[PDB]
Amino acid sequence: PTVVGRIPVLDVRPVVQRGRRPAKAVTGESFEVSATVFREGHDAVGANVVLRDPRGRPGPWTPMRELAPGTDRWGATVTAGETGTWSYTVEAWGDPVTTWRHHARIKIPAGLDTDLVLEEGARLYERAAADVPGREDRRELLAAVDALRDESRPAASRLAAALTPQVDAVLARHPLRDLVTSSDPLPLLVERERALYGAWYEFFPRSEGTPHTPHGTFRTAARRLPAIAAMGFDVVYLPPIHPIGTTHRKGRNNTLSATGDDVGSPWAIGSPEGGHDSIHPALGTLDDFDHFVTEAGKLGLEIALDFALQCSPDHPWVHKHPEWFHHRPDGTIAHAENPPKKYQDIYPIAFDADPDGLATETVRILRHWMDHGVRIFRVDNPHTKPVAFWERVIADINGTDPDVIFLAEAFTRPAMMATLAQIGFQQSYTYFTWRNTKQELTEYLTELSGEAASYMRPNFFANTPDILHAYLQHGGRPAFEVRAVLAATLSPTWGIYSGYELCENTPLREGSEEYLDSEKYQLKPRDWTRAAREGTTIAPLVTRLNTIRRENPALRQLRDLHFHPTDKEEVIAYSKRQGSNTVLVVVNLDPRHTQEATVSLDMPQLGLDWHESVPVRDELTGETYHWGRANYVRLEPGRTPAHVCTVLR
Amino acid sequence: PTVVGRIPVLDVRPVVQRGRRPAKAVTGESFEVSATVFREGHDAVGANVVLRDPRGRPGPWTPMRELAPGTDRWGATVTAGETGTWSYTVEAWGDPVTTWRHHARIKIPAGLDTDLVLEEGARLYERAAADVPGREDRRELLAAVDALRDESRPAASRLAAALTPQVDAVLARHPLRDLVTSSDPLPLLVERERALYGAWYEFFPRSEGTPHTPHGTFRTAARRLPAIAAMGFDVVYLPPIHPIGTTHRKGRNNTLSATGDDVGSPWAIGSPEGGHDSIHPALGTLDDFDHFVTEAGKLGLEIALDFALQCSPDHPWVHKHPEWFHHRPDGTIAHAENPPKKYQDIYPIAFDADPDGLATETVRILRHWMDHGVRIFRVDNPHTKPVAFWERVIADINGTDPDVIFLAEAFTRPAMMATLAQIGFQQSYTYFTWRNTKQELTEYLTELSGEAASYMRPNFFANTPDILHAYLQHGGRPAFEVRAVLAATLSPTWGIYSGYELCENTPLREGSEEYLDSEKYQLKPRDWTRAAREGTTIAPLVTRLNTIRRENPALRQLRDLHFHPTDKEEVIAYSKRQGSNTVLVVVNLDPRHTQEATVSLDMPQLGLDWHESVPVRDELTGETYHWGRANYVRLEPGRTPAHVCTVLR
Ligand SMILES: OCC1=C[C@H](NC2CCCCC2)[C@H](O)[C@@H](O)[C@@H]1O[C@H]1O[C@H](CO)[C@@H](O)[C@H](O)[C@H]1O
Ligand SMILES: OCC1=C[C@H](NC2CCCCC2)[C@H](O)[C@@H](O)[C@@H]1O[C@H]1O[C@H](CO)[C@@H](O)[C@H](O)[C@H]1O
């Protein structure tokens, strides 16, 4: 009982944890299945990929090619359809027609064994014809058999008849396959399209108040949705919406002690008004939330709720479930840290005393918000909770509600970010904000779209309430434009935190990535109408970007991405493709200085010969340009951060 | 039911084919088991490797360490004992005592929480005490427990009682391990030492004849073994010893037609005088072979036989089992090709008509030679036979006779060479002869001793009857010296084909790696006594080298090898280590010109601080040197090809 089959087929990728967790995909996504495929001796091998939908049904005949000569690595692109658990195998086989055609091309003109090789071809095309099921496809192949056998013709003419394109036609359709060897099935999990594609917008409802009641409510915040929808966003992510604690409530600018009307951080979940299943009374009731969810849905927006599995000391859990916390010998509970940060206002959950209780409560809490229209959750700080916990929770929820998308806010070491993705988290936050040079971007994106894409889906938020990167601080408005062009086109999921559009870039101090006067500890009213009137918002650019994404399916995917070399360190170029769609992007990473460069396009990667002109259209400017293997660009920051171009039919 | 455990243990290496084939080792070989290990939050993890011999017995406590900061990859070295099928797991755990000690060294001198931190520690040394079952070890920790709780002692003095190395012992002996998580078992296959370590000598028995009878016999050839054993070799590899066919027998110098007395290629196995189970009658009988095998053993030599699963057209199989061959439509059998080489004198075995029959006969043939003392098989050209055939045959033979070593002569693409190693082949031929620059050699060895060492064991033949590399052609005798030093110290198994020691370097043509007047097609008599008197043999160095290997266990293993930088392309340097043994080698790859260089030793890789003296002894000259972090060397071709140095304590 051998491990290797008749024709070796080994290391079928994609693979997640040696095959005991599923590789990932979404409806309509293309990705490449691959395998090492070879045989003993010198004869030709073929390989093909077999996709199975969740019922057993196989996909189209999908043949593979050797991906680089002499490597015996083969690949083919396959595409997932209906959501569910799929499977895929690679089949390998002896390819006798390629083997024979190769030998007949040398032996027949050399006059070697011409009578034997031609009868070999007759017998073998006859065999190819026994499986071809079309009467026309059959009779075509069998004519070549007779032409091979016609001794009244020169051998060169008899052989020629087995290589006419009408024979390659019938043969490409129904190939003759010897010694068919299958790999073991590998699991694929196909999820709804939002798992991979979508633009996210984060805002605090409490900041969208009125002059007479400054603390916003769901009813006042619902009026901010039209602006957000108009910018072309699909998901609206809310920070925790529940009662905020008062004990050790932080004051403005992350000061330890609050004051009389300091609002405190929404992540300090819990107070005697309720816990994670309740609404913060200054936002309104559970019906105010439904109104919000409904108004969001009407505009085409999906609500994503923040799940922070933690408590403020006033959460009812603190006394209702003391065993969900770790108490020091004096009975106090150390406040949470994500060092060097201190979270004095909240308690970390301990998991080893009553793991069943936390599991049951977590899914109850989540099913509660599920019942009210929440189908997406931004999981706060998952890497401080056990990995097997999220695995079990995501399984419970998805076993009944497979459409529920979880996003992992895991800024941490590469191991944990990867593991959390592989155990269930549909999307992941990334290091995107700390990749700002051409080389950092190229490296990270080469990886995220490389092998990582079989278990991770990146959500490129260009800012969060906790990350005001120095690139944006020092670059001003042209920095905010470049980073949005970058996030919206390098990932099929990107996002911004409210105030990005207004280019809010004042840090708490220098060397800090915190915001001065951070929204986390204060209401942050913003004059959206003034900013729009005065043109001091890049909301126009954010909108056209999500427009480009919605008209260009190349931008709705991640794995098909290629960087093109340019002769300036500050100028990056790259293209993505989906079928006939080819988007092509050139960004000036200098926020401060005009750059000009030669972008030397890798023409075959766009599907073109080395010398062809390319009709492109700069979807930001609407202008049209004619490019070739080398192209002069000039990008003036403030005027034009980048060209975002579709190739024209 | 989750995939990930409480404390994650992930991607445990070494692994072969996702765990469906065993990793390899030999009795007494050291190698590193490694794993990705981490946890949620900021407390410490520990991990250990649990190696199990074939009855289950677990090995010594083997704790692991993070291999680089922030990588979450952990490793520990394990050592194999008895032959058999072993298994190994990694356990990971929360390390609460390491976390507390970390907090106690910071908080206690600052005077922060001293009464709580000290009580946290007492309660926890109390917990380590419930697992120590000895009456004495318990009170040891409990005295630290009582001193930690001692209200009337200085805080610095209470902490000290939990940190005495007298307590570090009883804890390293019985560690407090929380939430112990295991990986699933991985299989390890431990083979006898000769599979990894040993020197080979290949020669043709028929070339050791008498003046009156030029075709040697086993009885005359047995007389050549004293020279071979004395040269320090362990294995004697004989080309096929069976009847040679006459149909299409090749003549001298690989000419297509023989003459009246051309002996033919020994690989043209088979005639009506017998096939693979029979002895070539010009060699003597099966009793002469017994005599030869027995006389070889007396000298400390093991016989390795060539197994070539193929036939001359006069083999009895050609008519007894036509189905083991591939027939053209007229019933003839195309002669074997390995393009561009043509082997007109032999037919390849075809495997798809009667695979059980070929298997049964194959293991029948091998058990015959096993019955006559042959426990090693050099499998000729395995990559022209199906991979699964070798898997099933090697499993079968080793299933009854686990000591039988197979060596695969597969010079081909890397995929095939890897798979044959992974399916059973104890040793592999390598690309060694085509790696002659410092960068080629370093690249290849970094690969062979890196991850490849978990499934392949290299046999560094510096020449074969089929590979006289141009390096040896153009370099002459100093080239032959350099490659022997290189082969004998870079691999624990190396070999030479007889005539190497006489520096036979005359090729078929320019641009060929074939031998002129190949022993493959003609008796090649050699005046061994004359060459030694005339000093035209490098047998002294071969002998010196094999002695150095036998006194220095660093040269009897493969994986511990490290390259040291030198400032001349032509001077390579490296060291190997096995326990206290450190061999350090500096070779001049220039065969024609004296090279001088500064060898800049990587002192930690030798186990020293950058300022230490290193007493070495040049095992080739007997000279003694005091070396350091940087060393000037001068190597003259002809006089000194290399330093091969042992370190002294
Ligand atoms: O829940 C903690 C939490 C985790 C998130 N993780 C960071 C760490 C890596 C860099 C970027 C994200 C973010 O801090 C943010 O979502 C959140 O913190 C906020 O809430 C706390 C509770 O009130 C306050 O104590 C704290 O000051 C305030 O910032
Ligand atoms: O057995 C096949 C074969 C393969 C081995 N593989 C080589 C080829 C690639 C580069 C170096 C290793 C070696 O050639 C050698 O063992 C063998 O060849 C010999 O056997 C044939 C049958 O008698 C003769 O026709 C031929 O003249 C003679 O040389």
Image: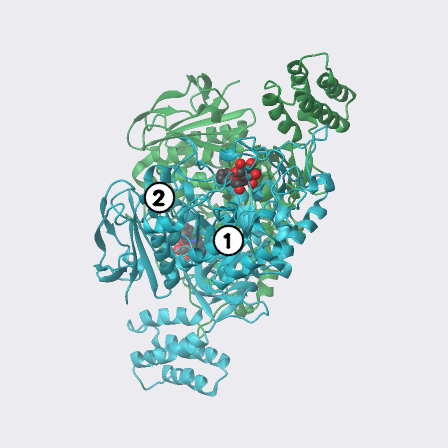
Chain colours: A green, B cyan
Residue under the image location 35 percent in, 85 percent down: B151
Residue in front for this viewpoint, A354 or B489: B489
Residue A262 visible in image: no
Image side of residue A385 versus residue A114, left or right: left
Rendered view: A382 above or below A127: below
For label 2, the crowd category at 10 Å Cα-Cα, with few meaning under 14, some 14 to 19 and many 20 or more, is many
Q: Are marks 1 and 2 in contact (CB under 8 Å)?
A: no
Q: Does mark 2 fall on the same chain as mark 1?
A: no
User: Which residue bears the numbered disc 2?
Assistant: A469
Q: Marks 1/2: CA distance? A: 83 Å
Chain under callout 2: A
| Three-letter amino acid code of the residue under disc 2 | His
Q: Horizontal and vertical percent for residue B439?
A: 35, 42
Rendered view: A228 above or below B366: above
Tally of numbered discs? 2
Rendered view: B127 above or below A480: below
Q: Horizontal and vertical percent for residue B216?
A: 52, 48
For label 1, the crowd category at 10 Å Cα-Cα, with few meaning under 14, some 14 to 19 and many 20 or more, is many
Residue A151 visible in image: yes
Instruction: Report the disc number at residue B220.
Output: 1
Q: Horizontal and vertical percent for residue B514?
A: 45, 36
Q: Horizontal and vertical percent for residue B263?
A: 55, 40
Residue under the image location 50 percent in, 28 percent down: A547
Element class at badge 1? helix
Residue in front for this viewpoint, A322 or A62: A62
Say if disc 2 is inside 8 Å of ligand 1. Answer: no
Element class at badge 2? loop
Chain under callout 1: B
